Image 1 (spheres, helix red, strand yellow):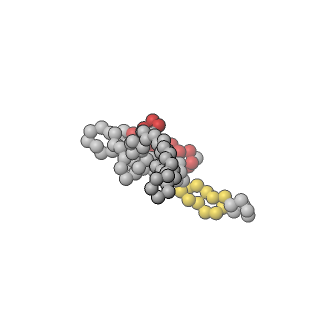
Image 2 (cartoon, rainbow over the protein chains, first blue to last red):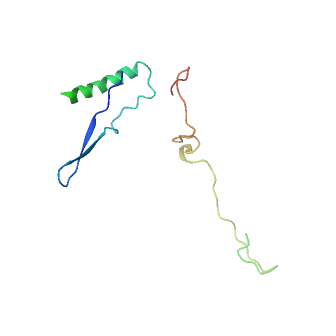
Image 3 (cartoon, each protein chain N blue to C red):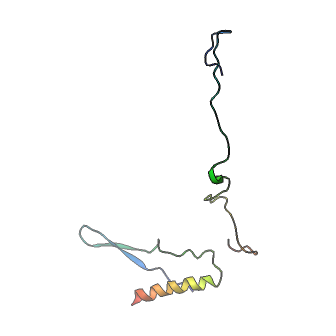
Length: 55
Length: 50
């Protein structure tokens, strides 16, 4: 019941190419001490940012 | 603490350095903050998560 974190791109300033893509750690909500009510609120705004990125 | 001394008698004294020992400012270090081996655990009962 958890959505996935989006893969963010890496821009190489010389040659302008893309240097691979890692997942977006550093923008992750630490839900590891939330009950069943806050976990649904946190995973809703994770499903909101994926819905923006799919558009 | 004997600022000088020649072998028994003709010594000169000097008082020791002043050394104030008290607690820290705001009691820093009394309480384990940011020590991942041993932290605090404020939570509800049935401690499933702090």
